[PDB]
Image (spheres, rainbow, N blue to C red):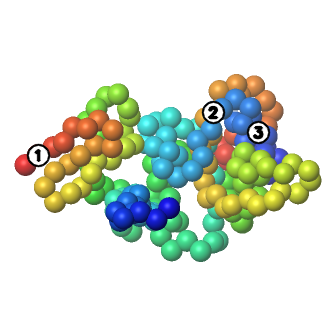
Amino acid sequence: VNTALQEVLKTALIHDGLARGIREAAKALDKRQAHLCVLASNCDEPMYVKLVEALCAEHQINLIKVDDNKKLGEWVGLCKIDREGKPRKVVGCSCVVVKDYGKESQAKDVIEEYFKC
Amino acid sequence: KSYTTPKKNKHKRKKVKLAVLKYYKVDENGKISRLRRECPSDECGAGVFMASHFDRHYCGKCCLTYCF
């Protein structure tokens, strides 16, 4: 869910097992060095959706759907500037790759049992 | 300042736009057949690509130019 995604991205921020962006995310996918992924659908994506579904239809790549590109960029560590309340300017991200190691948490179990369903 | 010689300008680089999307050829079936060659070095994995020029194939970092 949303709070489980926030927890796993905060664990990625606290344990540096994170691969943001597009180029290094696809590189970590092709390196067999990935655990989880997300995706932002229903946007202005003429070719990006078909390229990323070809990229994620490879080896049990998990996805979490989200409406906008905006609130994904708050719990990932994108624009951690002006922390006095609301953020100043957060740019849009599409997908992120998480390869957490210290996964002794309830939220990982919740999201993984949600994935095996 | 104002000098007699013409001013030398720095390398005004061009901005890319979805480069790897031009090399992952995707059809309506389950095929991900690529347009660019992968790396032959075992230092890294299989993520980076090589240069596709008209007469040679250059690395990103291995600097192993492939001739014809």
Q: Nearest the camera: B7 or B61?
A: B7
Query: What amino acid is found at the position of numbered circle 2 in the picture?
Result: Gly
Q: Position of residue B32 (x, y in %)?
A: 35, 56
Which of discs 1 and 2 lies nearer the camera? The answer is 1
- Letter of the chain that mark 2 sits on in the rendering: A
Total labels: the figure holds: 3
Disc 2 is placed on an element classified as loop
Q: Is residue A79 left or right of residue A23?
A: right
Q: Position of residue A95 (x, y in %)?
A: 60, 54
| Number of residues whose C-alpha sits closer than 10 Å to that of mark 2, classed few (under 14), some (14–19) or many (20 or more) | some
Q: Is residue A27 above or below residue B35?
A: above
Disc 1 is placed on an element classified as loop
On the image, numbered disc 2 is attached to which residue?
Answer: A17
Q: Nearest the camera: B4 or A117?
A: B4
Residue A18 visible in this rendered orientation of the protein: yes
- Letter of the chain that mark 3 sits on in the rendering: A
Toward the right, the furthest residue is A85
In contact (CB < 8 Å): disc 1 and disc 3: no
Residue B30 visible in this rendered orientation of the protein: no
Name the residue: 31% across, 28% down. B42
Report how far apart the C-alphas of labels 1 and 3 lie in the structure.
48 Å
On the image, numbered disc 1 is attached to which residue?
Answer: B67
Report how far apart the C-alphas of labels 1 and 2 lie in the structure.
39 Å
On the image, numbered disc 3 is attached to which residue?
Answer: A10
Which quarter of the figure has residue A69? bottom right
